[PDB]
Image 1: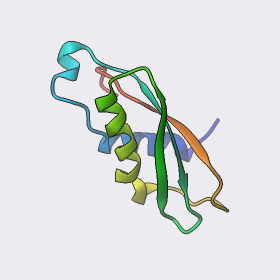
Image 2: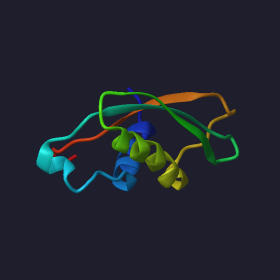
Image 3: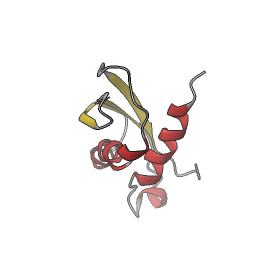
Length: 92
């Protein structure tokens, strides 16, 4: 299995914003977001590919990547990445 990626998925979720009515009306889901880390240590090029959930959450999941960017590992070259981002009314 992976390692460091599980822990940034946490730091991203800790910066990620969920709306004040969403738990009350039962809203959840998973957003697919494509991006890259540079070998220079910065994060760029964040774009949403797919979602099963609110387009208001899709706008928040993409920003959460930039918002946790100082926690991230360094690649050996600037390749590509394509990552799913999750929400829950469950504590997580």
